[PDB]
Length: 159
Image 1 (cartoon, one colour):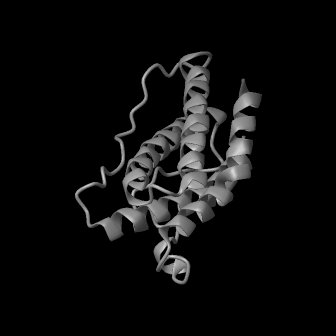
Image 2 (tube, rainbow, N blue to C red):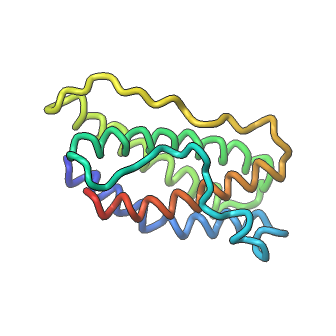
Protein backbone atom coordinates (compact mmCIF):
# COMPACT_ATOMS: atom_id res chain seq x y z
CA UNK A 1 0.00 0.00 0.00
CA UNK A 2 2.69 2.50 0.96
CA UNK A 3 4.02 1.79 -2.50
CA UNK A 4 0.75 2.58 -4.27
CA UNK A 5 0.58 6.07 -2.83
CA UNK A 6 4.26 6.47 -3.56
CA UNK A 7 2.99 5.77 -7.04
CA UNK A 8 -0.08 7.95 -7.12
CA UNK A 9 2.02 10.71 -5.65
CA UNK A 10 4.29 9.90 -8.55
CA UNK A 11 1.87 10.22 -11.47
CA UNK A 12 0.27 13.29 -9.96
CA UNK A 13 3.64 14.95 -10.12
CA UNK A 14 4.04 13.66 -13.63
CA UNK A 15 1.00 15.67 -14.65
CA UNK A 16 0.89 18.46 -12.10
CA UNK A 17 2.96 21.05 -13.93
CA UNK A 18 1.32 20.03 -17.18
CA UNK A 19 -2.14 20.69 -15.79
CA UNK A 20 -1.03 24.04 -14.44
CA UNK A 21 -0.15 25.26 -17.91
CA UNK A 22 -3.43 24.01 -19.25
CA UNK A 23 -5.25 26.18 -16.77
CA UNK A 24 -3.34 29.42 -17.28
CA UNK A 25 -3.55 28.74 -20.97
CA UNK A 26 -7.34 28.48 -21.07
CA UNK A 27 -7.65 31.64 -19.02
CA UNK A 28 -6.15 33.61 -21.88
CA UNK A 29 -5.52 37.31 -21.31
CA UNK A 30 -3.97 38.33 -19.10
CA UNK A 31 -2.66 35.26 -17.34
CA UNK A 32 -0.06 34.28 -19.93
CA UNK A 33 1.71 37.62 -19.81
CA UNK A 34 1.25 38.04 -16.09
CA UNK A 35 1.71 34.52 -14.74
CA UNK A 36 4.20 34.99 -11.93
CA UNK A 37 1.81 37.67 -10.67
CA UNK A 38 -1.57 35.87 -10.67
CA UNK A 39 -0.59 32.21 -10.60
CA UNK A 40 2.07 32.35 -7.90
CA UNK A 41 1.84 29.67 -5.23
CA UNK A 42 -0.04 31.72 -2.69
CA UNK A 43 -2.88 29.63 -1.28
CA UNK A 44 -3.18 31.34 2.10
CA UNK A 45 -4.34 28.71 4.57
CA UNK A 46 -3.11 25.79 2.51
CA UNK A 47 -2.66 22.62 4.63
CA UNK A 48 0.73 22.81 6.40
CA UNK A 49 3.38 20.19 5.75
CA UNK A 50 6.56 19.14 7.45
CA UNK A 51 9.00 16.70 5.90
CA UNK A 52 10.83 15.36 8.96
CA UNK A 53 7.95 13.76 10.83
CA UNK A 54 7.12 10.26 11.95
CA UNK A 55 5.67 8.44 8.96
CA UNK A 56 2.35 8.54 10.80
CA UNK A 57 2.17 12.32 11.07
CA UNK A 58 3.19 12.82 7.44
CA UNK A 59 0.03 10.92 6.53
CA UNK A 60 -2.19 13.09 8.66
CA UNK A 61 -0.93 16.11 6.78
CA UNK A 62 -0.92 14.48 3.38
CA UNK A 63 -4.51 13.55 4.00
CA UNK A 64 -5.59 16.98 5.08
CA UNK A 65 -3.76 18.38 2.10
CA UNK A 66 -5.20 16.00 -0.41
CA UNK A 67 -8.62 16.84 0.94
CA UNK A 68 -8.03 20.56 0.86
CA UNK A 69 -6.70 19.92 -2.61
CA UNK A 70 -9.43 17.82 -4.13
CA UNK A 71 -12.02 20.10 -2.64
CA UNK A 72 -10.22 23.12 -3.98
CA UNK A 73 -10.08 21.42 -7.34
CA UNK A 74 -13.73 20.62 -7.58
CA UNK A 75 -14.33 24.33 -7.26
CA UNK A 76 -11.95 25.02 -10.09
CA UNK A 77 -13.79 22.55 -12.30
CA UNK A 78 -17.28 23.82 -11.60
CA UNK A 79 -15.90 27.21 -12.46
CA UNK A 80 -14.08 26.27 -15.62
CA UNK A 81 -17.07 24.52 -17.14
CA UNK A 82 -18.94 27.83 -17.22
CA UNK A 83 -15.93 30.02 -17.83
CA UNK A 84 -14.08 28.24 -20.58
CA UNK A 85 -16.53 25.69 -21.96
CA UNK A 86 -14.09 24.97 -24.75
CA UNK A 87 -10.94 24.24 -22.74
CA UNK A 88 -11.19 20.48 -22.87
CA UNK A 89 -7.60 19.34 -22.50
CA UNK A 90 -8.05 21.23 -19.27
CA UNK A 91 -11.52 20.15 -18.30
CA UNK A 92 -10.17 16.64 -18.49
CA UNK A 93 -6.90 16.92 -16.59
CA UNK A 94 -8.88 18.65 -13.86
CA UNK A 95 -10.99 15.56 -13.38
CA UNK A 96 -8.13 13.32 -14.25
CA UNK A 97 -6.39 14.74 -11.19
CA UNK A 98 -9.43 14.79 -8.98
CA UNK A 99 -9.79 11.05 -9.55
CA UNK A 100 -6.22 10.15 -8.78
CA UNK A 101 -6.55 12.30 -5.70
CA UNK A 102 -9.60 10.34 -4.59
CA UNK A 103 -7.60 7.12 -4.61
CA UNK A 104 -4.85 8.70 -2.52
CA UNK A 105 -7.44 9.67 0.00
CA UNK A 106 -8.76 6.16 0.53
CA UNK A 107 -5.20 4.85 0.56
CA UNK A 108 -3.61 7.27 3.02
CA UNK A 109 -6.82 6.76 4.95
CA UNK A 110 -6.58 2.99 4.93
CA UNK A 111 -3.03 3.24 6.23
CA UNK A 112 -4.42 5.52 8.91
CA UNK A 113 -7.54 3.80 10.25
CA UNK A 114 -5.57 0.58 9.87
CA UNK A 115 -2.30 -0.40 11.53
CA UNK A 116 -1.59 2.90 13.25
CA UNK A 117 -4.83 3.74 14.95
CA UNK A 118 -6.21 7.02 13.67
CA UNK A 119 -9.91 6.42 13.11
CA UNK A 120 -11.02 10.00 12.67
CA UNK A 121 -9.11 12.92 11.20
CA UNK A 122 -9.92 16.60 11.45
CA UNK A 123 -9.30 18.96 8.55
CA UNK A 124 -11.74 21.86 8.17
CA UNK A 125 -12.17 22.23 4.42
CA UNK A 126 -10.62 25.28 2.80
CA UNK A 127 -12.40 28.23 1.22
CA UNK A 128 -15.64 28.01 -0.74
CA UNK A 129 -14.69 30.57 -3.36
CA UNK A 130 -17.87 31.30 -5.29
CA UNK A 131 -19.26 34.70 -4.36
CA UNK A 132 -16.13 36.41 -5.66
CA UNK A 133 -15.68 38.32 -8.88
CA UNK A 134 -14.96 36.01 -11.79
CA UNK A 135 -11.45 37.39 -12.21
CA UNK A 136 -10.90 36.32 -8.62
CA UNK A 137 -12.27 32.83 -9.24
CA UNK A 138 -9.74 32.38 -12.01
CA UNK A 139 -6.71 33.82 -10.24
CA UNK A 140 -7.12 31.68 -7.13
CA UNK A 141 -7.91 28.65 -9.19
CA UNK A 142 -4.58 29.47 -10.81
CA UNK A 143 -2.85 30.12 -7.53
CA UNK A 144 -3.98 26.78 -6.22
CA UNK A 145 -2.71 24.89 -9.22
CA UNK A 146 0.66 26.57 -8.86
CA UNK A 147 0.96 25.74 -5.20
CA UNK A 148 -0.21 22.24 -5.89
CA UNK A 149 2.61 21.72 -8.34
CA UNK A 150 4.98 23.49 -5.95
CA UNK A 151 4.30 21.29 -2.95
CA UNK A 152 3.39 18.06 -4.64
CA UNK A 153 6.97 17.76 -5.83
CA UNK A 154 7.95 18.16 -2.21
CA UNK A 155 5.47 15.52 -1.15
CA UNK A 156 6.99 12.87 -3.41
CA UNK A 157 10.43 13.27 -1.88
CA UNK A 158 9.05 12.25 1.51
CA UNK A 159 7.26 8.93 1.10
